[PDB]
Each structure stands twice: as C-alpha cells, then as structure tokens.
Image 1 (cartoon, chains in turn red, yellow):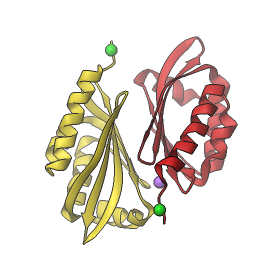
Image 2 (cartoon, chains in turn orange, green):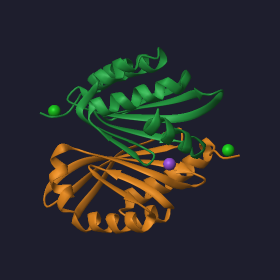
Image 3 (cartoon, rainbow over the protein chains, first blue to last red):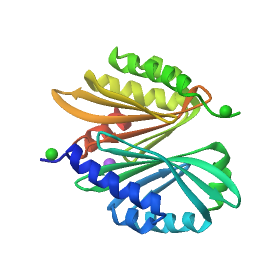
Length: 121
Length: 125
Ligand SMILES: [Cl-]
Ligand SMILES: [Cl-]
Ligand code: NA
C-alpha cells in the first residue's frame, strides 16, 4: 500500500545501473522525485531542479566513469563508481532510496581527497 | 594508504549490529568520528557529542528494536531496523560510512509516516 516490492526496486536499479554504465546522466535525473533530497559532503540539495543543476555541474568536470559495483538493499540502490577529473581518479558511493517508483533521497559518499575538489565543482 | 579492508569494515559492522540488537547506543557513539556527519530527514548533525544527544533522544521513545538485515557495501554498513514507538512499528535504514576505523558519516532513511515523529523526537526529545 506504500512500499515497493523487490521486483519494483530491481527495475529502478537496472535503469540506474544502465544509466551509470552508459554515462547517461539524464536517465538518472528523470528518476528523481520532485522534492528529492541530496546529501554530498557538507553540501545538501533540495528539489529535482537543484539536483539536476548539481548533476550537470559535476558531469562537466568528469572525463571518465567506471561502475565498480551495484547492490540493492531494501529500497536502497547502491552504486560504487570511479570518476576521473583532470587526470585524477576518485571513488564515490551513490545510494538511491526509492519511494513509489522514484528516488526520494540520494546519499553520496566521497573520499576526503575529493572534498577539496568537490567544493570547486 | 587511506582505505579500509573488507575485514576491518566487517568488524565494525558486527559491532554496530550488536549495539542495535542489544540496544546499547553508547557502543555506536564510541564508533563515531568526532566530526561525524548525520543526516536524517531535514535534520542534520555534526560531531559525535551532537550525534550522541540525538541517539539518546531517540532511545527515550524507542521501546523495541529489531534488526531486520545488515549488509556491507564497500565502506558502507547498512542496517535495516524496525523501531517501535508508542505501539507503532517503523522501518528505517541506517547507513554508516567508515573511514580510518570509525564512522565518518551516517545516512538514515525513514518512511514518510515517521518523518513527523522523528522531527519531534530529535528536536524536543
Ligand atoms: Cl506498499
Ligand atoms: Cl589505504
Ligand atoms: Na526520503
């Protein structure tokens, strides 16, 4: 009545996984709920518009994307990625929490070395 | 030079799991980095002492804890729990990101029905 079956979460996982693998950010943005909450480093973003703006900014600095692993846990889709920015490689973890077929919350873990870089972006 | 092995992460996972199941928050607080960042709903907390305060507030209202499932993903420990508050059961997911043997960041997913309740507890508990 308000939750998502494993099958439903898996469908969104496949979409997210495919989008990351193709380096296709627009598919992921379309999966965000209008009031999506994004947490990355000290920064926090509210709303799909703010999230889309942030995603586009980040992707402009990213020269290469590699998907290391993807896992589903309850209504959470976790994606471990490596981004190349200016010849340097950074590992990040994206967690997508799904409600009603869309992503309500995004938690992004970034390494301390990327924190300095991420402030610029 | 800066990472944690799967074995070290799993050790902390076991500690976190035991603390939840046995209902002993001080064990969790002891694993938090001094500058731990916690996000739950609209609330945000910085520092272990502040996180400790939030944990104590919550535990005042939580009458039962059930650890439904636990998984390790890279340096993230995810714990799915059910909390009982005032006779009602809520499902939550706690994600603990580990750095250098302690938890640097905590991300908590809560269902929309719990959102109002959690704001009361964390602000006014
Ligand atoms: Cl449901
Ligand atoms: Cl290391
Ligand atoms: Na949410």
